[PDB]
Image (cartoon, coloured by chain):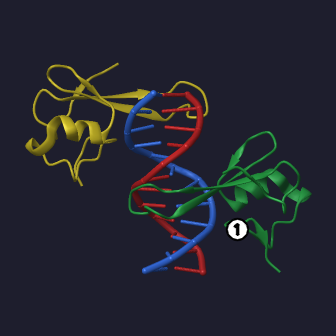
Chain colours: A green, B yellow, C red, D blue
Amino acid sequence: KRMDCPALPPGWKKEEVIRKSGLSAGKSDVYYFSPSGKKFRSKPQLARYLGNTVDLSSFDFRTGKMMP
Amino acid sequence: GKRMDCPALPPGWKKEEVIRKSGLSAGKSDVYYFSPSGKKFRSKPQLARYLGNTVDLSSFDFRTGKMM
DNA sequence: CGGAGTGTAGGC
DNA sequence: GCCTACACTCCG
């Protein structure tokens, strides 16, 4: 599932992957992809990439949604 | 490279550490193991399978070659 | 040597 | 005790 993520700029996509095994079996990891395709696995990695082009203070990494 | 006797596995067992010379993981290493026959092992689950019940590798640290 | 998938420390 | 964030494995 490579989903657009409306609350980021155009081209940015979100993907949620189910862990198949280990002690976190059934938990999920959320990945984001830039228009170029670079993969991001956290909020600060995403903030380091984006800088002041986007405010991410209210941005929920898990859901891809801004939190009012 | 250098196979050095790994005193924590049965006798005849050699370890070898090989530095990655470039790319993103430049300067990390892969650790390899050799049986007496000289089969190369690249992981802890593969080493466990070859050995099964004959050796308890639960406390075995694959990277260092020591117990834990 | 890469990198998807899992381990796991530390903040909470 | 749970989650975030990123290190590390393992096998291609």
- Residue under circle 1? A63
Residue B37 in sight: yes
Residue B7 in sight: no
Q: Residue furthest front?
A: A1
Question: Which chain does the numbered disc 1 sit on?
Answer: A
Closest to the observer, B42 or A68: A68
Label 1 crowding class (10 Å Cα cut-off): few <14, some 14-19, many 20+? few
Residue that appears at 84% across and 63% down: A7
> On screen, B32 above or below B62?
above
- In the image, taking residue B18 as reference, residue C4 lies left or right, namely right
Dividing the picture into quarters, in which one does residue A38 lie? top right
Residue that appears at 14% across and 49% down: B56
Closest to the observer, A54 or A30: A30
Dividing the picture into quarters, in which one does residue B18 lie? top left
Closest to the observer, C8 or C4: C4
Question: Which image quarter is the C terminus of chain A in?
Answer: bottom right
Residue that appears at 70% across and 65% down: A61
- In the image, taking residue B60 as reference, residue A54 lies left or right, namely right
Find residue A27 and report its horizontal and vertical position in percent.
Answer: 50, 64
Q: Secondary structure at mark 1?
A: loop
**Three-letter amino acid code at disc 1?**
Thr
- In the image, taking residue C5 as reference, residue B50 lies left or right, namely left
> On screen, A68 above or below B51?
below
Closest to the observer, B4 or B52: B52
Find residue B44 and report its horizontal and vertical position in percent.
Answer: 29, 41
Residue that appears at 74% across and 41% down: A37
